[PDB]
Length: 338
Ligand SMILES: Nc1nc2c(ncn2[C@@H]2O[C@H](COP(=O)(O)O)[C@@H](O)[C@H]2O)c(=O)[nH]1
Ligand SMILES: [Zn+2]
Image (cartoon, rainbow, N blue to C red; front, side, top):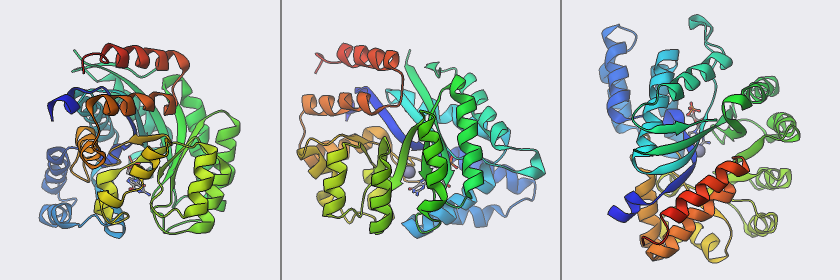
């Protein structure tokens, strides 16, 4: 829909390597096949036929990482993701990515993130502020649930060093059937005690103890919340933690059986803060405009209700007050139009 495409939007939950253009992923595959590193037909088959249920999508991510883990590619896809979000009028983007180590190519977590910064410096089609369309970009560093406590601490230390190029917080993500909260809690507590903002993937699978322990940590945001129970909802509503809602992702991974029963409607009606997000618009073949369209249809929102929802996301960002004031100005300058 045209007016949804033109709506200024805020993206808080987008994984870099889950946001790659189809043609770019297949071009990387083709180039690596011409070098003999992979069998192009096999990789292409996985990309087309992986059903992207919660179990299968992490195998897909292993394949994506075999295609994308080198400095030049990280720079390229960072630029492409930012340009794609800006062209659908995302005015503020928190981009999250897991820094990667790869000794065989001389990649450290730090040099991975430097390739991300290089990608932001190469953005040309739009105006960008990371510390004619204009987009504010800020960065979240992801801890993957496969990692050790010490490796998670390395990521937190890097985030603290990189506050000067717009890192604002830390994410916990990766396969929810892997790893234990006790592994990551000490590193996340260090991050929080050093004033980094914290967002947690929470309740993607049934796990009552882990959900309660993540809620008691009091992160600044959580993502998904698909298998919360009533005591979980009560605690979340009392702590006022915003929820990153990923409609398409949830339906495809089979974490929520349909949009008509999705908890985002309850949160909306309970006046609990929620933000519509893409999660992985490349993996799940969507866009932030389409997520808004699904939500507007399902809830039956008017233009002005949709605009109020979009604007409310400003106070869930991890950005400094000056940036929030600028976002308020932008949204107000798009306010009386509709
Ligand atoms: N738990 C979880 N992690 C995800 C999801 N989508 C992307 N990720 C994380 O994001 C990574 C891909 O983006 P990256 O951090 O490599 O840029 C995946 O390997 C995974 O750890 C998701 O739906 N659930
Ligand atoms: Zn996610």
